[PDB]
Length: 86
Image (cartoon, rainbow, N blue to C red):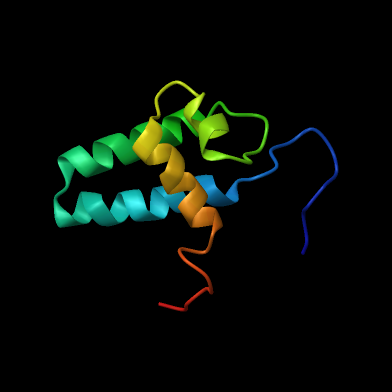
């Protein structure tokens, strides 16, 4: 832990950086549609200052939707129950 400063800065940066990791996966598999909706959601968070708490609060941001909303929460739930090392 070198950085981490309690000043004016984001609070998540986790779900966003990850939403990109998966987005790249689809882009490689040749998913123009999937990568379109995924990256679009990331664009919305690119302007989001306050953190996330619920799916509805996330869907309130332009550029996202319902399916994506719950998608974000899923990533916060480690997927299901416990985390796995792929």
